Structure formats: C-alpha cells, structure tokens
Amino acid sequence: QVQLQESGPGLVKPSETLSLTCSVSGDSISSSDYSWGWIRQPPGKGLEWIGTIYYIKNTYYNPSLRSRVTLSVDTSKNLFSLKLSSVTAADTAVYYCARERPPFDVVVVPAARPYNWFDPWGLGTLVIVSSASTKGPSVFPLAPSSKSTSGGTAALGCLVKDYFPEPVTVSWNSGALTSGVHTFPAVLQSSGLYSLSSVVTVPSSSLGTQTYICNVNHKPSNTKVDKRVEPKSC
Amino acid sequence: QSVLMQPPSVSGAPGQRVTISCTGSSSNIGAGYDVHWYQQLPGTAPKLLIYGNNNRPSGVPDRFSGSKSGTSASLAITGLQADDEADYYCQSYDSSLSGSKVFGGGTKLTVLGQPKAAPSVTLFPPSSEELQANKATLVCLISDFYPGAVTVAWKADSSPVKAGVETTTPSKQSNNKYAASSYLSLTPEQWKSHRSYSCQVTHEGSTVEKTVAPTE
Amino acid sequence: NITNLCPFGEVFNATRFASVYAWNRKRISNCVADYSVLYNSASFSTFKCYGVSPTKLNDLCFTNVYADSFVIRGDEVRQIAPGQTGKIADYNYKLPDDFTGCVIAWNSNNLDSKVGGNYNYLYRLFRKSNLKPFERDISTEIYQAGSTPCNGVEGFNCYFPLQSYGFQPTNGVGYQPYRVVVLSFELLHAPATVCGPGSHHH
Ligand SMILES: *[C@@H]1O[C@H](CO)[C@@H](O[C@@H]2O[C@H](CO)[C@@H](O[C@@H]3O[C@H](CO)[C@@H](O)[C@H](O)[C@@H]3O)[C@H](O)[C@H]2NC(C)=O)[C@H](O)[C@H]1NC(C)=O
C-alpha cells in the first residue's frame, strides 16, 4: 500500500506562486525505483502533466510549463513539492500528485522513463486562482426573440454575471414558476468572477399575458435582485 | 487541447461491448511508446486501468482490455455495467522537441439507462441592458439531450473563437435528461465587428448550430 | 589435423545478447570456417555480404574473424550496412564504407520480447559526435544538450544518454527485436589463420 496526500492553499491571487506539498505513506521518496509526479485538471476538462522528480535531484518538466515549474524533495518529511510561478486564471485546476513507476523487471531505471505510468494517485486538491473580492452579481434579461414566439414554446432566462464567491440562488416569480425551469451551474471566468444562467421554457401565448421575474439571491454580498424578462424587440 | 485524440463520448447498453480509441502520431504511439489508460469515476481522482498497452493491474476486472496498432491504441470494455460510467484517459510519451508525457482529451463512457435524445439549442445575443453597461455576453443554452456529453465550438464569421469562452459540464434537469451552457464574453466593439456568431453543438457525432447577428 | 570447426554456435546460439550500445565482439581464429552451413543453419531474415562474393566465400582465407553481436529493432536492421545513417549507425554501431564482411540477422521475438514487455535492451539516443567505424560507446554520462552543465543530474537540456526498446510480442515487426551478428574478416600482412574448407589450403 502506497498513499499520497496533497496539501496546498485553496485560493491564490494572480501573479503569485502556487506552493503544493505531497506527503507519501508506505514508501520512501528517496527511492531509486519510483519517481514522483504532478498532474492537473482544469474543472470540466482533461488531464495535463506538470512535471516529475526522481531520486531527489532529477527533474523532467512539461515543456510548455518548464519555465514556471520547480519540483523538490524533502527526505526528512518524506514529501515532494511543486511550485508554480506567476499563476493566472488558466492555472485554476485540481492538482494531483502521483507515484510514477517504471515497467517491471527494469535494470536501468533512467532509460525506461518514456514507458513509466502513474500509480497510485493522490486525492487531488482544488486550486482557484482569483484576485476577486466579494461582489454582487449583475442580472441581465435573456429575452425571448421573435423566433420562439412564432412557434409553440418560448425560451427565456436570466444571466447572473460577475459575482464572488459562490453560491447564488435563482427562483422564478418568487417560486410560483417551477416547471420548465433549469438553473445551470456557474462558470468561473478569466476575470476570477462567477456567472450562471437560469432558463425557463414557457408557452408562447403567455408572453403578453404573464409576467416573468427571476429572483436572484447572493447571500455573501447580501444582494437580492428581481429582473422582469419581456420580449423587447430586436 | 491534447496531443492524443479520443472520441468525446462513447455509449452502450448494459452487457454490450464498447471500444474507446486513442489516436496519436509517429512521434508518440507510432514511435514505439506504450499507452496507459486511467479511469476517472465521477468525483474521484484518476486511477490506473491499463498499463503498457495491454496489462491489467491487480483489481481491474477481466472485462477491461487494451491493445495498440500503428499510431493508435484501443480500450475495450465487455459486459458493460453501470459501475463503468466514467471518464477514460489514454496517456503515452511524445519524443518531439525535448520529450513529454501526453494525455488524450478523455472519453465520457455512458451506460445507456434511457433513450438517446438530440440537444435543443438556444442562442441569446447580449441584451441591450448589458450593452448599455458596456459589456456583451452571448449565451448558448443546450437542453434535453442524452447521453450527457456534448462538444461546444464558437465561431465569429466562421473563425474559431477560443478566448472568452466558458462551458459547464452537462448536468441533469428535472426530466432526467441533460443540459449544458456556454458563454462567449465580448466587448461591445468586437460584438459589433462581426457579421454573425455561431454556437455549434456536437452530440454523438451530429452537429447542430444556432446563429446570431448584431444587425438582426 | 585442424578439424576443429570455428565456434560460430557460441556467438549465434548465445542465450543472451548484448544491447547495441554495448555490442559484443568475439575473436575467432585458428579454426576452419564453412559459411555454407551458416547460410543453412537457420532461417535468417538478413544475410548480406560486402566486399567479397557470397558464392565462393568458402574458398577464402583471412588472418582472423571478429563476430560482433547485439539486438536492435527490425526497422533498424537496414542501418547495419555501409554508408548508412540513423541513431544506430551514428551513435551505436557503425560499419565503414569499405566494409568487407557479412551482416546476419534474424527475428528474436520469441526470445527477447515478453508479455508485459522487456525493456532491458537499450540504445544510445544522444552523442556529441558520430561513431567512427567499429568504435563502441558504453558511457552513461548525462548528455549536456545546452550551455548549462549537468553535474551528473537530469534536468532540462540534461538527458540520460540511453533509452529502452519496448519489446512486446504483439508489436509490429518493425518494432520487434532482431538479433544481429556482424562478421568482419581481417586481411593483415600475416599468415592466414581462418580458412574455409574449400580453399586450396585444405
Ligand atoms: C544452434 O543450435 C541449433 C540447435 O541446437 C543448431 O541446429 C542444429 O544443427 C545440427 C548441425 O550439426 C543439426 O544436425 C544435423 O542434421 C542433419 C540432418 O538432419 C545432418 O546433415 C547434419 O550433419 C547434422 O547431423 C540439427 O538438426 C540442428 N537442430 C535444429 C533444431 O535445427 C545450429 O546449428 C546451432 N548454430 C550454430 C551456428 O552452431
């Protein structure tokens, strides 16, 4: 059994240095057989190798990140560490450490490095890069255009833009409208602020008859906003 | 963006066989380097599934198999079970420039538990309220699709737009089908500098697009 | 009385072969060498001779013969020939342009690959200059690709000079292991000491 445990600050401001530490249990980081690596995953996206350190001093870096990556080993704490300089919003990701092992029955470990795989993996730690202070959202109407109006159903909604931190709650007509409603999870923008949208599918013959208000609540900033959504012409 | 190319989604009924390809080039898989496969269950870290093209670590069931041929590799899953719904990643080594480990873009495997459904797409231009606030956001809302896997691509006068785009992972709505959203954030200047913008939504290999124009 | 056949099975039937970067050389002298039985000893994928005609090799004599042996992958057998270039010819085993000898090779997938992979056959990937004919580089010094010295440590622009082949049984033939034996014939201003049966010496 080998276990790896990440640890790092959850939030870092842009241009700062991200420092992460991975503690190894059930093995020695002074190994001349195994290497120790970092991989990351932006929320909702794929995996990206950061770099690897082997036998205390040997390093191998992702070429597109090499200038910003520093790896090191502390044998007294049985851990290895990652430092990523000059972070931007593109560096918001879950960071995993992993043991990188060579194929079985290998005599010359450094010669087999291209055939290494990752096993086991740590639990991962989410790092958000943002300079955002707590801030209330702006609410804009997503009006039903002349398109859906011509048919049977009509889609309309509310854009809840540039708030921090999460979460924000959205209802419609103070909770009196619930069917056909879907409120999406938030995206984190490169500004370091969140946005989400809430949509409702409604009968087209209701657009003059029925009022449609989205109620938006952002408790951290103590902000509440009602927005009426009407079919204002092009 | 990833150096190894995987299909974004694969699906099969419980008990069927399923394959996930992983195509590289003569500088990685075609250069003789091994392919490893990791399974990422939802909410969990990746875990080793296949190593060295076709070897199973202890604990990985018989139903998983791997192979490689030329510049490509393949993960096969027989007797599909609900436990198998996950994202699968291939990984190899690329010798170009100074050398680097490379990953595929990942494949969402869906074990079918309901009928397939093509997405409905609605593209909202920036509201006049937002434009008066000196901002522009195009909102592309996608709903009522299954499996919950979709690829979103934005175009400004047929030119692919990468920056200013953010997209949510498909999540279930009240009828248990899936929905997703994508945003293109622009300044008003660049909003009005193009004839039209396209939100293109690819689902199970079929692409539907919606278009908006600042004039219309 | 010199009825002792040359010990070719010692080289060809050796249970283990060397990596190409540390290729082996066996000195063979003071014996009789029929090459017909070599060209009939097994099914060789490659059997090319340079400098002397392969028809009447048996009617020739030489001071001594050297048998170099190693493993490479299939697509690299073509580099074991005069005038060739590539990582093997440049960095691992180099034949001269005026080579006189024979290159013999056969597929060893049944011996040198294994399920899960055999990664213990290595080749040299980096070198500051090309090998001269028949020279050998067994060093494992970190390769300094850039302006900053390596101090025996791997890093950017500091690379371990050797790399594994990945030999698995289901590899394409171009990536399967091949055992290679190179026969060099030394013609020196000295009495012959290796002779074929069909020469008028015998
Ligand atoms: C490497 O080892 C193999 C196997 O031990 C050698 O092949 C063997 O070669 C002998 C040659 O003396 C074969 O015996 C011959 O049989 C024929 C008639 O079939 C006869 O005309 C010969 O006089 C001799 O008795 C033997 O069958 C053969 N074995 C196999 C399995 O092919 C091979 O020669 C060795 N290589 C070298 C370079 O020494």
Image (spheres, helix red, strand yellow):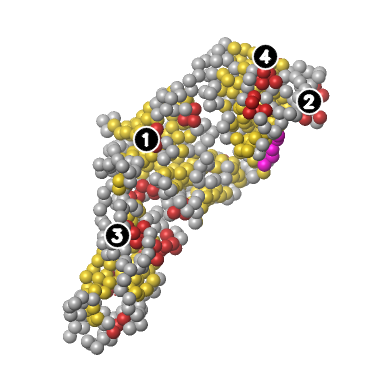
Label drawn at residue C131? 3
Label drawn at residue A203? 2
Spatial CA span between label 3 and label 1 = 46 Å
Residue shown at 28% from the left, 67% from the top: C68
What segment carries the magenta color?
Answer: B207-211
Marks 4 and 2, the one that precedes in the sequence: 2
Spatial CA span between label 3 and label 2 = 81 Å
Residue C114 visible:
no
Residue shown at 42% from the left, 52% from the top: B33
Label 2: state its secondary structure: strand
Instruction: Tell whether label 1 touches label 4 (CB within 8 Å).
Output: no
Indicate the chain on which mark 4 is placed: A
Question: Could you say where residue B16 lies in the image, as x and y percent from the top left?
Answer: 59, 49
Question: Could you say where residue C47 lies in the image, as x and y percent from the top left?
Answer: 37, 73
Find out if the beta carbon at label 1 lies less than 8 Å from the nearest ligand 1 atom: no
Q: Kindly identify the amino acid type of the residue bearing the numbered disc 3.
A: Leu
Question: How many numbered dots are placed on residues in this image?
Answer: 4
Q: Kindly identify the amino acid type of the residue bearing the numbered disc 1.
A: Gln
The foreground one among B40 and A187 is A187
Spatial CA span between label 4 and label 2 = 21 Å
Of badges 3 and 2, nearer the viewer stands 3
Residue underneath mark 4: A226
Label drawn at residue C39? none
Q: Is residue A75 above or below residue C62?
A: above
